[PDB]
Structure formats: C-alpha cells, structure tokens
Length: 29
Image (cartoon, rainbow, N blue to C red; front, top):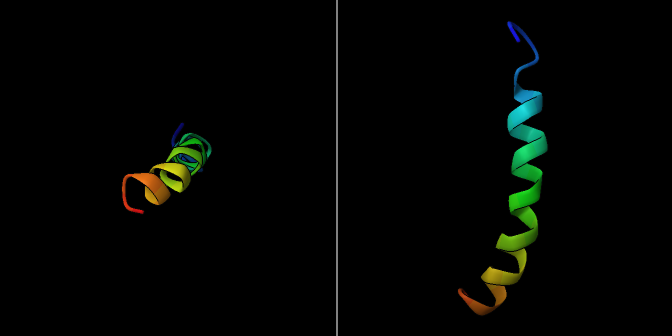
C-alpha cells in the first residue's frame, strides 16, 4: 500500500456520499 493508497479513501469515501446526500437534504435541508 505504498502508492495508489487513495483508492481506499476514495472507495470508502464514495459510500459517505450516499449518506451525505440524504442527510444533506434532511439534516441540512
């Protein structure tokens, strides 16, 4: 995991986008 480690953050972060999307409409509506 020396290089291209961003893959983990990008792949995992992509999941957050799902919640942030809805939470943003309700939590930040």
